[PDB]
Length: 237
Image 1 (cartoon, rainbow, N blue to C red):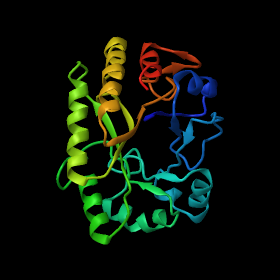
Image 2 (cartoon, rainbow, N blue to C red):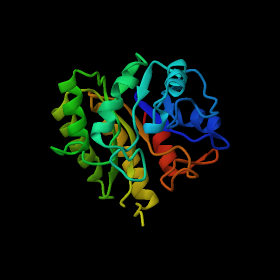
Image 3 (spheres, rainbow, N blue to C red):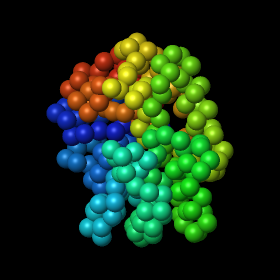
């Protein structure tokens, strides 16, 4: 059990979750966003940005789970759009949930010295803060069977830098117009990447981006119908 999925509350979500065999899910929110999921599909709450850092939002998260994902893609202007200093300065409010705490999930550069995740993990340890595990994202631009090894190399480098277990909480082949793989390239990468992740013992969990093609053109399902990437993911774990 590592395999999960990001999900919007799209029409057919509960059937998709049951068909694909997600062992957990998240919604980019402090609660399941109207998603009904069976036992054996653990919900994992998230504080997405600077605006969800309020006693109400944190209370809600804490009612909903034992494990908390911090800010989503703070390194991107279009997402949490947050300085390292702001993330560390809020960190104590997230510690106050008492929940098992995942780092903010950078879109890029997690292995880069002086980069966003490096500076956050650096300051967190210097201040004596708690970062129980490191959510990561990965958007591969090489759409060949080489992508799996590239993700492997990224994952190993991050784990080597910080020595915390990893969740791969949002990954796909996508290059930023966004550029996309063929269906066959995508399905083969779903297949190869999940087999590699199943073997990577510091990776506790992974989640393809995303369950529904209504959320992202890299989606596994259209309504309750899996495409060939969804079939690979159903079979992945």
